[PDB]
Length: 82
Image 1 (tube, rainbow, N blue to C red):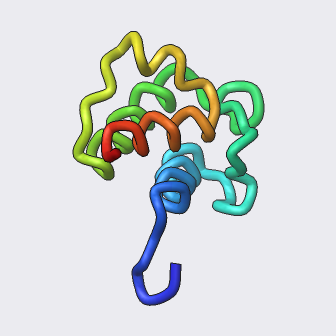
Image 2: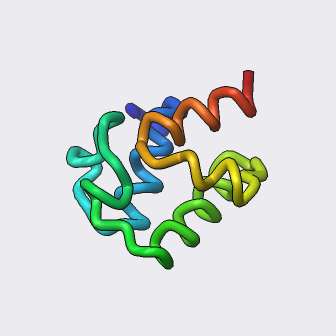
């Protein structure tokens, strides 16, 4: 966002864009990491870790299995903040 302001949504979308090597603009909330954004097994392992670091949160491996979309990653991060 302007002058370094950024929402949880924008921060998830930037981390996903960086990790999966796609335009921030192709990272919409409806997107599947695997089916839409071409994440392989290693991409997903590293993406979990990049989200954990950005948001200073622990995503347990079995929660991480269910986070199949950009929307789920936003809702998980928002829930472990509020």
